[PDB]
Amino acid sequence: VYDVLEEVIAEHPVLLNRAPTLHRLGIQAFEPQLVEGKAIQIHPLVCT
Amino acid sequence: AQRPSLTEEVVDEFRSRFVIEPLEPGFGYTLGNSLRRTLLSSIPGAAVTSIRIDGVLHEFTTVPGVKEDVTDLILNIKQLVVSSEHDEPVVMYLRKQGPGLVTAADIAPPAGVEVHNPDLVLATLNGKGKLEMELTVERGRGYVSAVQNKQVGQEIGRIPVDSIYSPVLKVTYKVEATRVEQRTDFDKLIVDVETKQAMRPRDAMASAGKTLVELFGLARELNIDAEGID
Amino acid sequence: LIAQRPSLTEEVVDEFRSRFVIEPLEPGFGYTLGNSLRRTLLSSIPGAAVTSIRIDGVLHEFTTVPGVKEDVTDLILNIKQLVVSSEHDEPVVMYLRKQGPGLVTAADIAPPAGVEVHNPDLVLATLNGKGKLEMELTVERGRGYVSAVQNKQVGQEIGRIPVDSIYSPVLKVTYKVEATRVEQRTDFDKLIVDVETKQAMRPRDAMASAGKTLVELFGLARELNI
Amino acid sequence: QDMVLGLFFLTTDSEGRSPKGEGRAFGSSAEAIMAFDAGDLTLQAKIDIRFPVGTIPPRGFEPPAREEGEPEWQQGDTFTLKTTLGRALFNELLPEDYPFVDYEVGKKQLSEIVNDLAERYPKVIVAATLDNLKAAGFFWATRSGVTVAISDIVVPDAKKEIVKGYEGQDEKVQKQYERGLITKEERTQELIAIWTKATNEVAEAMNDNFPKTNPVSMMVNSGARGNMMQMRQIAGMRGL
Amino acid sequence: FLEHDDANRALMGANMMRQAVPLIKSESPLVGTGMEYRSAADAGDVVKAEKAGVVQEVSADYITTTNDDGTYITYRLAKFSRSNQGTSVNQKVIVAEGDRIIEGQVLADGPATENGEMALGKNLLVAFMPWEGHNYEDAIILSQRLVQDDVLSSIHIEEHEVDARDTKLGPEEITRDIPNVSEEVLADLDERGIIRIGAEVVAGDILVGKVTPKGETELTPEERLLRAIFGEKAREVRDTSLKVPHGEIGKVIGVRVFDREEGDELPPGVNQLVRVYVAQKRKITDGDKLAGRHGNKGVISKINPIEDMPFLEDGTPVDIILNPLAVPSRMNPGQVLEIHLGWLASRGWDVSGLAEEWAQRLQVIGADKVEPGTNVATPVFDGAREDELAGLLQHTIPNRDGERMVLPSGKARLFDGRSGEPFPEPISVGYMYIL
């Protein structure tokens, strides 16, 4: 099941979004990689 | 788990990539940095160490007949790769007359000593040639700094040139994660190295492995233990 | 140039904290090897420990054994850190029984044949006048560390409490690098690898296991080319 | 934030950073890294390096090309420059065509670089450039030696005399005010001016105080995080 | 150290120092202030002895004491009981069965309290560095030590209050007889329809078996004729069973059963009431929010082995690592001093007559000689100063003959667990209290 999930997360843009979308560059797409844990992980130069 | 192994990827005849298979967590660092430093400062070889440019003084900047200045002579000669089977300081000669340019193909080798880059361009000359100097090949390992070797003291003509006995020239070691049966935190080692034309990197792997295996057998010999591996 | 091959020794200062010295080492070459030794010593030297408890009269670890001062969860968290030494591949069932007012020290625990407990100086619990205490301890070998949850394997026995395990017979492992005074212009250096182990193995055998693992690894790396 | 701090440490100068191996000349990147490993080449040390065919040199240094009769056709000839190892290690991240960079690449400069790569080079190359910049920044951020201990936060030595003089002015103002020849509003505005001047003077004193390599100085000057006001708050004066 | 922050950070710390879950091995901080004892005693959950005398017994649950007046009192203790949100209020003993007690002495401790002092968090060793960017922008990276020691782990108690109603289609019963279910799902269930008190529960289980005796499910004339032709009477009952929520694990802490038969108070219709409490233990994991006492907030980024994180000169690793870019910008330089004092406490110092001004002051205070572990108390606005902290770090007890470990200016020559070489320059390390 997790193997197929790692397979399916590939080639699937995912729309990350935050609450107060003040400007246009507030909702974007990303490619998901199946990290362990219980939190979503983000690139360190889209946090602006 | 599964027994790891090694794979090599060829890109050119001077640099190559090595991959050490998915490793147990943390041990990627047990391998990488030690492999880097052992490849760097363990394997020996032959190199220049001191030369005698004829008819010059340290207070004199350039040299007549050759527009090339002293510093770039050092920079051009220290790149001369050389192998030896002598193990003591030899002294060998290099001369040239007439206009043109002196390259790496007109140096009269002594017994046993061989140079592996005959196409190296050394200097350019115009008019009267009068080029002659003697260079000293030594054997050693690592990278020796330009310390005053007390050769200038007894003779003005002596000048010491630093060298790189090490076949390896540049090294890059990294660790990256991979999935092995729903286990992703496992590590995996990458080592990409550029080694000069003296010998292929795989022989450097052999020699570094010999050194490391010896230096850890020196600790394994304390006893015989039932640890469990392979 | 220099043919002085490395040479190992062994210095002793106390029962377990032992430092092993390698004098003929290349300059700027001891730190990575010391790191290698520390890594393999901190997580690659097997041992043994206690895997689960089975008390009678207590089905879950959130009640208290009748007439027992410490809880069941506290008993778990104070038994999981035992100091033992086992040799059998299959896990062995060790027993403990007590009654009446008396601290149940680890000495009171009964080691079966082939398994030992190396520390009887443990204050597990202090019973009261009506103590009727019984305990079972499964012991197994391994290496590293395991979390409590995955240790559970069987549901047919319901009252048994599964807990974690610590397969690590070792403590702080430091080292140092000194300057060799040999008359060589490279100014060789010297490595002093410290090791400490609680009471299970000895530093000689601990480093023997470490050397065995690292020798296997670098022999693989050394020979598998071609 | 920190990536720019890493790049700034990589591509800074040797101004008071304990140079090691100055005046020497090297032949390539290999010798530079060997001298770095052996522990005789400071990362930010003024050294003369030869670069091979492929590198596009700086701009201002070209008209000072090598004085020789033959045509020094610059765009494919190996050359020699009085560089620093940091710039040499920074240049290979930027693509094979970007002209050499020989200035402290702080906050805004990195933005100038990205603007140029965005308008000239395609998107994927800019992505690779940003990723490599990130890797180098984090690497040298780990191995930078910037860590907020309690010795980093400086105290301007002259701030004490600054505030003592300005409170001398304040107490003269108050000794007059209790006499009544001035009003409360006048005193309040005069104090506003007095302590605004005090705040600015302590700000410039803190500017003078730090060394270039002090971590907080590296944060403010590299445009990593914060401003001058927040360092005034931390180390100098918080302001009215 | 509340005088070394900004108004917003003290406000944030005040707000976010009051949503801390309790911990199993609750312990007082190494560094704190004298409003843990008072704030844990004047509260309620700690049991106290209001009678001077001598204890007879301190058993599992009931601490039995005999007074000087000569009366027997059975102090019952709140052993693993539930609170409003679903945490645990577990009480524990502090004394033995041969001790004298005076009035108003803490004969036990409540949750998040040890020895009668408020215990919210734990003490962990910190090293201030940017490290691979895993702590980029005010985040936190932790060591797996605190997954083995269970230093930072908590226990929660969910509840379920289910009950059957008389309805109109016959009275609902609480029975093991759930229509057409496998024997494994009700194996834990009791004959009356409650799981065994102690067996585990996970998402996808059954808590209480409930069913409505009658039902008008499908009785249209076509289906009535079909059933008559078949000749078999299908079961009109329907499962009204309780259901553990999907996304929770736990183990039962207790069960309570009630019925209209007893004098209990219940509105009409309700037949049988069941209250099943479930109690789970959670260990610290990446993504679980953490914080500190100066609002230095953050979330766990990644968990690494013990050796990956650095180690000092004698081999002891570091427990937590924080990004030093947040300290200046966020404007809270009141945590560095907490870290330094925490280290000073965790390796006891020894100021036996240094003759310095600060030494004389700290001596007339009397807090000069300290063993390795004595928790330190710092007033909120009369806490530790600076030069005293520096001198204390200068004159700590040597590990060995002359081994004063960290340099006299806070920083420490912390090595690099990853590679092995020392980091280019020293690092600042100590001990901090983490909620």
Image (tube, coloured by chain):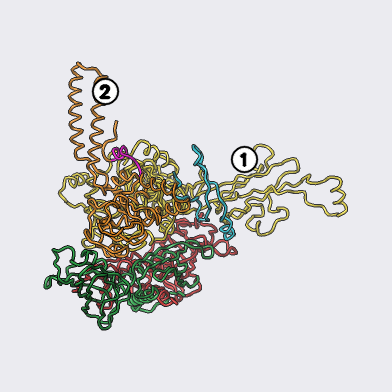
Chain colours: A cyan, B green, C red, D orange, E yellow
Q: Quadrant of the C terminus of chain D?
A: top left
Vertical comparison of E414 with A44: above or below: below
Q: Chain of mark 2?
A: D
Relative to residue C198, is residue C86 drawn left or right?
right
The answer to whether marks 2 and 1 sit on the same chain is no
Q: Nearer the viewer, residue D133 or C3?
A: D133
- Residue D227 in the magenta stretch? The answer is yes
Residue located farthest toward the front when viewing the structure as drawn: B127
User: What is the three-letter code of the residue carrying label 2?
Assistant: Gln
Residue identifier under label 1: E264
Relative to residue C137, is residue B49 drawn left or right?
left
Q: Secondary structure at mark 1?
A: loop
Residue identifier under label 2: D189
Examine the rendering and report whether any part of residue E374 can be seen.
no
The stretch of residues the image draws in magenta is D224-234
Position in image of residue D232 (x %, y %): 28, 38
Within 10 Å of disc 1 (Cα), the crowding (few <14, some 14-19, many 20+) is: few
Position in image of residue D53 (x %, y %): 35, 61
